[PDB]
Length: 126
Image 1 (cartoon, one colour):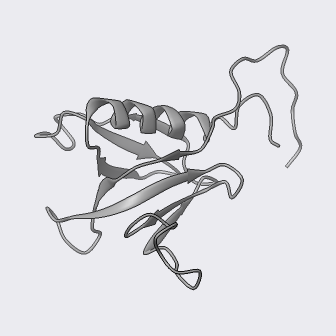
Image 2 (spheres, helix red, strand yellow):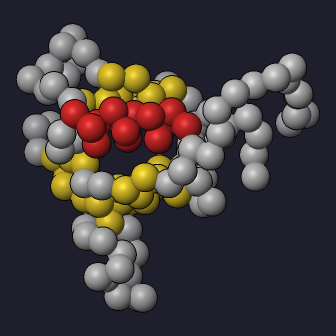
Image 3 (tube, one colour):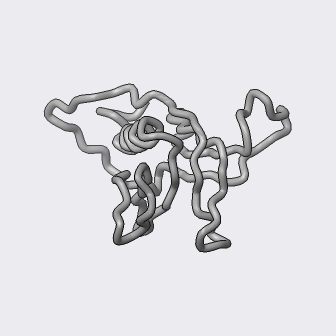
C-alpha cells in the first residue's frame, strides 16, 4: 500500500454523477445495455440500474457494477476502437476498455469528467 503525499494538488469534490449510458453487453458485439449509471464516490464504484433507484424498490439492485479500484483513466474512445460514435468514452482500467454511449455531448463529457474525478479521487480520499 503505502500512501504517498503530494506537494500541492488541485481539483476536488468529484461529485456524484447520474444519467443513462449504453454499455456494450459483454454478451453481444453490437447490442448495448441501456442502464442508469450512477457515479458513486462514497461507494467508490460504478452502479448502473435499469432505471432511477428512486423509482425502484428498496429490495432492488444493479444489473452490474464497476469498481473504481479498477478504472485508471477515462478518455474519449476513437474511430479505431469504436467509431460511429460521437460522444463515446472508454473507461480505461487494469488493462481493458469499456465502451459506453452517452445521450448528448454534455452527459458524455460530464461522465468522462466525473469518471475522471472519481478516478483521480481528487486530491485525497475521503
